[PDB]
Image (tube, coloured by chain):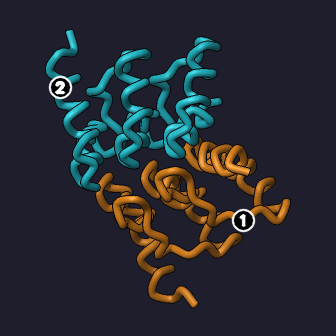
Chain colours: A orange, B cyan
Amino acid sequence: SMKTVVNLLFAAYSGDVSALRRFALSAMDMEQKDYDSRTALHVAAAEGHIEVVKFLIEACKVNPFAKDRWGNIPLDDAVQFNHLEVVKLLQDYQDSYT
Amino acid sequence: TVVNLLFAAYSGDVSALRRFALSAMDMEQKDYDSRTALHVAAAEGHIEVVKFLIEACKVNPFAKDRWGNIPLDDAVQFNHLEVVKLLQDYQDSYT
């Protein structure tokens, strides 16, 4: 259970879009959080993996307003670490989110 | 095992941590956010876990996570006073 959440989040950490796809293609909840309330989109945005953020936004359609332990959404990490291609994507996706 | 460590720290599972330390796995290994077992345990305020990590395993209390934060920083933010005192005394004596 939590073993997969970490495989999921470690796949987002490495920029492995294919591994994320295999997780998503098995009906796994892609919005699950870890011990720090961090999601796959959190780790992707913090690392600046533009293609990983794209997949979680377009293919999985994950909630971008999920807050971690410190109350931050994935956009906050992209802003703090100067990943602006991810910032612009999360900006546009947050204004249209459902 | 990379986070079975950190999932045990989050849940205050001192017994699981003792089993993992016996198998000689790295108790200071970090995750995707550069978080250690001491980080998560201090953030949750689980006192018996940070006791075991500093007194038995003697982990480095100056390890910084992705946000440059020390395990004591989370314990201060979330009002885990006894954990703050343990790490503060341990950080002073760290060789």
Question: Circle 2 is placed at which residue position?
Answer: B89
Query: Where does the C terminus of chain B fall, quadrant-wise?
Result: top left
The residue type indicated by label 1 comes to Asp
Asked if the residues shown at circle 2 and circle 1 are in contact, with their CB atoms under 8 angstroms apart, the answer is: no
For image coordinates 22% across by 48% down, the residue present is B76
Q: Secondary structure at mark 2?
A: helix
The residue type indicated by label 2 comes to Asp
Are there few (<14), some (14-19), or many (20+) residues within 10 Å of tag 2?
few
For image coordinates 50% across by 38% down, the residue present is B9
Residue A73 or A22: which is nearer the viewer? A73
The image shows residue A19 at horizontal and vertical percentages of 74, 48
Q: Residue furthest left?
A: B92
Above or below, comparing residue A92 to residue A22 in the picture: below
Q: Secondary structure at mark 1?
A: loop
Question: Circle 1 is placed at which residue position?
Answer: A29
Residue at mark 2 to residue at mark 1: CA–CA distance: 42 Å
For image coordinates 74% across by 51% down, the residue present is A1
